[PDB]
Amino acid sequence: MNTVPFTSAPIEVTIGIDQYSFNVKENQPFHGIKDIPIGHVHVIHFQHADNSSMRYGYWFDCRMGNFYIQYDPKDGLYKMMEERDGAKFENIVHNFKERQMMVSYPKIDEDDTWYNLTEFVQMDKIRKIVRKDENQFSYVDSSMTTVQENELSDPAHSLNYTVINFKSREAIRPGHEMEDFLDKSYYLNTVMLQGIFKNSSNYFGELQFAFLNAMFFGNYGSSLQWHAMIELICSSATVPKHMLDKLDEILYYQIKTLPEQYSDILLNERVWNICLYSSFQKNSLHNTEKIMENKYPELL
Amino acid sequence: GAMNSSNYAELFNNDIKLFVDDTNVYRVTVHKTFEGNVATKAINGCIFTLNPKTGHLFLKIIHTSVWAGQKRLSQLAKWKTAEEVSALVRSLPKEEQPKQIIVTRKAMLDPLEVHMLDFPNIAIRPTELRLPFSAAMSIDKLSDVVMKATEPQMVLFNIYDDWLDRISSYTAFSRLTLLLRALKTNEESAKMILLSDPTITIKSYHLWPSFTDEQWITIESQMRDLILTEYGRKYNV
């Protein structure tokens, strides 16, 4: 169980850790989050009390170094930073623990929610989507645009998701226009899985990173990448059985976790109605279709 | 975006463009089977590809053999239209290829876009205009060449005959949409008007009668009347 100490909390702020959040008052004696489960990626995330605009946060894995949070009063945000001095870091953490100035990652022992949402997400894959190679952690916010949103304007602050475009020479073989447009199996299986992602685990990792970025930061281009990656599987006639079974499980926990009140902006009516009711895989997502109908019958 | 009455003069500028109409690609007669079920029998069709500026009609005849052993024919017809248009574009010299293709039916946009990926600078546009190109098969010489065809064939026509010698492309297109609207609303009445006088003939190399400017006014007047009569009936008003 690992720790992210905070130097201080000079501004009032709603702090997110994975699917949890805690309000901290201006100059409250808050010194961090302890008991963070080893084995998963985590996201620590912020929404300032004064400006409820720009949600922002850091993706990290505690195995990859000692990370802390320190407010920068020049740039006006909570920054993640790595402490390279192991003995200084342990000395900081132990002091704040003794003084009980840290909230405990409030995991119920039965509750596999974070594991289910991050099953295929790996820090190495996040650091290729969010390029900043001098840090072991990744910064995302509400406003960051995707490589794809840029084409249709600062490359260094971009989310580099895999570009998916159903009306592209990449998606459509010369001489198989109708076949490839109506049945995306070639695009899914040869171009994306074999060619670009190498396997379904990398494809699902990116889909789940896309969802979590949409959910935690209201990142619009993230939401578009999540839906595009669902649509590409559902619109394929030919999909390995294990991928359909896994997709059902992935989607169930994303829909289960979605705050009930954001489904209007976070869920794309056209895509979900097509995936569940019109597509090749209309009958192949029992769990997702049952939670979607019981929790969001308005959308459908 | 969409071609409407607000940008109607764009049709007659010096940017090459083509209307595509797929409403006569897939044509059927519905009939009863011996066991009293229903069945369709395809007939020859055509793609109606028009330059509105010049009157150059590219009539791709769709022979019934293209449907043999194929499924979801009305879907396949959109894609086969977009294939043939894409083939026509590639067959034209660069300086003749259109900058815009206007489809008369929104269902042709995605098929045409996907077949034209190789041509990113050619704009595929819908139209809010209700164009009467469906009645193209009420023109006797076009109907004849489609129905006689024993194989896939492209036939080149000028749908304005020699009218551009005397009138502008705006006025030629207006005359043409009025004749087609008339043939579409009452085919019998429309054809009667066009051939009621035996002394006005269709030249071998033409589609419509050899009318003098005055006779065209009389004809256009008779076509307008015919369209209102029929409208006054449809709606009893």
Image: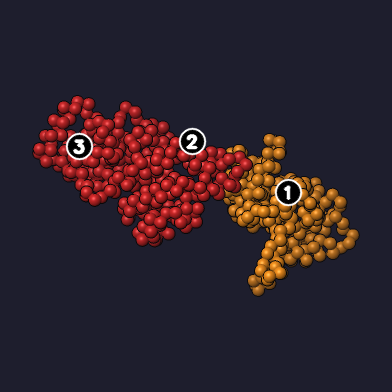
Chain letter, colour red in render: A
In terms of depth relative to the viewer, which is nearer, B166 or B90?
B90
Residue B12, horizontal then vertical, whole percent: 68, 46
Chain letter of mark 1 equals B
| x 9%, y 39%: residue | A99
| Label disc, if present, on residue A195 of the rendered structure | 2
- Name the residue furthest right: B199
In terms of depth relative to the viewer, which is nearer, A114 or A169?
A114
Q: Are discs 1 and 2 less than 8 Å apart at CB?
A: no
- Name the residue furthest top: A85
- On the image, numbered disc 3 is attached to which residue? A3
**Label 1 vs label 2: CA separation?**
39 Å
| x 29%, y 49%: residue | A113
- On the image, numbered disc 1 is attached to which residue? B60
Say left or right for A286 vs B115.
left
**Label 3 vs label 1: CA separation?**
72 Å
Residue A62 in view here: yes
Chain letter, colour orange in render: B
Say left or right for A44 vs B12.
left
Q: Are discs 3 and 1 less than 8 Å apart at CB?
A: no
In terms of depth relative to the viewer, which is nearer, A158 or A289?
A289
